[PDB]
Image (cartoon, rainbow over all chains, first blue to last red; front, side, top):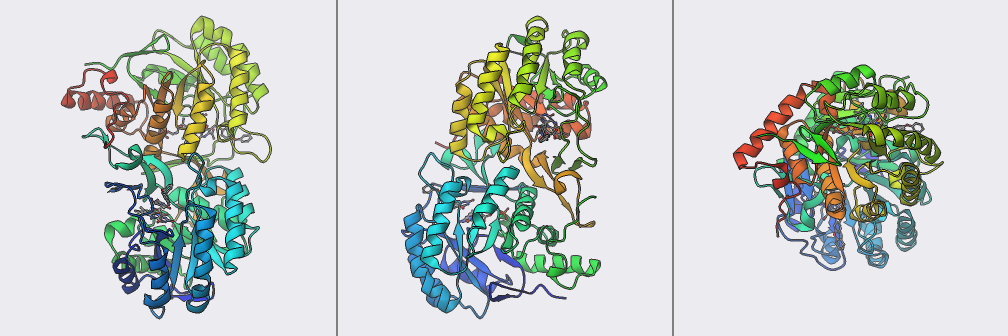
Length: 313
Length: 313
Ligand SMILES: Cc1cc2nc3c(=O)[nH]c(=O)nc-3n(C[C@H](O)[C@H](O)[C@H](O)COP(=O)(O)O)c2cc1C
Ligand SMILES: Cc1cc2nc3c(=O)[nH]c(=O)nc-3n(C[C@H](O)[C@H](O)[C@H](O)COP(=O)(O)O)c2cc1C
Ligand SMILES: O=C(O)c1[nH]c(=O)[nH]c(=O)c1CCc1ccc(Oc2ccccc2)cc1
Ligand SMILES: O=C(O)c1[nH]c(=O)[nH]c(=O)c1CCc1ccc(Oc2ccccc2)cc1
């Protein structure tokens, strides 16, 4: 009875890892995650140039989840490349490197230089398709024209196996169209569903005030709020993308959340808000919790139930 | 002291009402809704001919909220118009009628026949733009030109003041676009935000099964899950539609959920999932709690804090 997986030519102790943005911005952060029991980690989404991000407060958490508008605070690509290149201990667990260029050309340059490190060290690319486009347009994943462009270009530039981090969709025609774009691109080996539920608004009853300063308090939702929307996207894309892996991200607080996520067809399972709240000790708990779910049900491996959610009649 | 207000040339005993779909399909239900302390009611969305809807189970509720895919079960527009014109007691509260016809022409035929009863009897139109779209395309409000035609045609057909039922958006650029479309139409004097969060998927860990029968388990999300989505949309549209009203809907279990909604610009507060679980008694509770929030804070009127959510600079 194990949590083990072999995927994308790499070996993982368990399906669990952090979500891009959580405990992965600094070298201190990255080493923590590497010292945890996570089967993997992913670096904070980066840009060419370092960024301080938006004014604080810019993340707030509650019993039922999190709201954020961080604004891509990151140490910039050169650090994140150097860490993959010379600092990270691959003998511990695989590394994923997230990128979120503010245009097709910024992302292209980054993958070009990332190519030879991926090849020689095994660092894996998660292209974050919630990267901004021209302001006054939806983020790149809600604009299927620009999304096509970005992947045409990154494929040519990178010419290695990579992955995409997607927002949630809420209409069947959107699942249909987005999977169709993805399926044009054989090098997209995995798909991560979902990013934060876009532009929610949390209001404090006593103060009669939004809780985060940027964007008049509007921001991305994570946590218990988004788990059903997260399972839908996982399973939609699991259904419509049979040559590609899906990684689940969305309100995982427990082995059960993880278990459901896997049932929908998740391969790896990322923890965002909960990891931020609870800390890296969360991964031992999750591992134990899922294993006690599989023991009771008779499951020895993940592939025995991955994608095997039942429907009625 | 008391929450009574005036919108659209009507008197209301308080800002509370059911949400289209909940406790409003049968004559029985609408008599029940009428007999309750709600300030108003609205009838199940309807089509020209009656519909049976999709296979049960097609609604389920859990602690954080609900999932459904009813398939627009309804007694049919002839019944609801009869209720509006020969059966509703207008001295008790105002009545709102919801239409969700399967085409612009289905909708046109209904409003032409509704407009005379609106003139004389004062029923109020709430048009459901989560209604179906042409082949390969997402629901109408998620296809803005299609949305413009529906409003162009209904406005021409109806030619009295009316309102619209919106699904949530998740992008600023969509707020921007969607609001603009709505501002093209002066007869749209109120906007109801938001409809259920499209295409979530609840999975049961013990059965390893989805919980509702249609759409392989996928349906709309209501309840605690969507409150931070319903407030952003309430506020997004309140700010972008100064000459209109906004009706809030989504995640009201308490006076506090209500208070925030109002703070976010909301004139009427709709109740759906919580109404469906607790029953119409909820309306006496929701009054009391809101009144109690107002007292502690020293508010005498809804007008005093409506739309007054404080931003951090
Ligand atoms: C503070 C914070 C920072 C995040 N930063 C990133 C990021 O840099 N890149 C990215 O692709 N996703 C980012 N996300 C999205 C998360 O990866 C995740 O998809 C989302 O929070 C939902 O997961 P959760 O429900 O576990 O929080 C961030 C989320 C939070 C809360
Ligand atoms: C069983 C059920 C039936 C519904 N039927 C309709 C409908 O006919 N028309 C409509 O506009 N919305 C319908 N809705 C959506 C609600 O009016 C409301 O937008 C949604 O429940 C969000 O509010 P909540 O958070 O209180 O659930 C329905 C919701 C449920 C749960
Ligand atoms: O870091 C974030 O703010 C963030 N939060 C999330 O929940 N998901 C994400 O993917 C990210 C990073 C993606 C993102 C979010 C806001 C951004 O803000 C802009 C920065 C520059 C130009 C336009 C928008 C840029 C990237
Ligand atoms: O009745 C509902 O299922 C429902 N549930 C919601 O949460 N919000 C709603 O607005 C509605 C009614 C709107 C609706 C839902 C499903 C529909 O299903 C179709 C019927 C025929 C063709 C295509 C879709 C049509 C209208």
